[PDB]
Image (cartoon, rainbow, N blue to C red):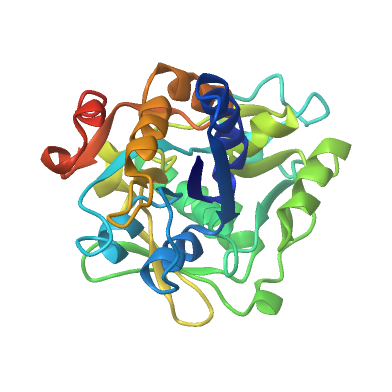
Amino acid sequence: EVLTVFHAGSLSVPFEELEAEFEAQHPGVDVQREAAGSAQSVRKITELGKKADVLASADYALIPSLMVPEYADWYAAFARNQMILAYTNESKYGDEINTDNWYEILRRPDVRYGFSNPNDDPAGYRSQMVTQLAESYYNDDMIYDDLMLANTGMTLTTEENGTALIHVPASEEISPNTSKIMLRSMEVELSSALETGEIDYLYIYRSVAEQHGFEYVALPPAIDLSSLEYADNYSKVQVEMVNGEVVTGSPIVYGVTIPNNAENSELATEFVALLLGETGQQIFIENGQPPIVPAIAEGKDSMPEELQALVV
């Protein structure tokens, strides 16, 4: 039989490992994964009329926003990403750097750091969010100014409600000081630059750092966008992109559901049980995407009995 799984691209490595283990436990089963962007994966079900047994989004909130109640009765937040500061043995002051002093290292004139385009890449605007949130955490109101405002065409205003608003101009108008910053649209250019020592530090997800074998500084959960419990702190920063669209600091949390129109719901239950259980947990730990344990569910009383045992 066949199990159809639509998942976010960033879930590819762990879901590959899940496919292998699930097929090893279930001989006759053919797991057919489709990797795409999270919103695209959801739209396949909600707009294109495609049938999937499992839907996994890199933004859990897309499930209640777009699928509930017509296509989903429940969802579970099961893992997260986290913003880190990646480096290598070639990075200046790598021996010194830690969670307490990372921004002080970045302040040094000879240190160069990379981040993605904040207009086009979530990792890009997230680099700005994390840096701004650092100010309240470390009691230093010049971190964002020194690192970003002084070296780019990005600006900052304070909204009437106390929220920090970062303004990103046209990509060609960001015009970074290249002695301090490497800014790229394609993240692989930045990871390559870190590998060769062209940059010293790189704002990227933990998953990416671990995949490349980079060292990294773990950042406080209050600022690193990893934790559901710090959602109200993350929301204290917003980023306005050139087009006018505004994004808000929020947890980077993965969500899963079995769609209401799944063709093999019973088999889907067993797959999600593997994902939420000890096997899936370790797989996600190993890919730098820490699991939420137990997973946090909405619509728990509408979930299969087997899955209810695996959620809060």
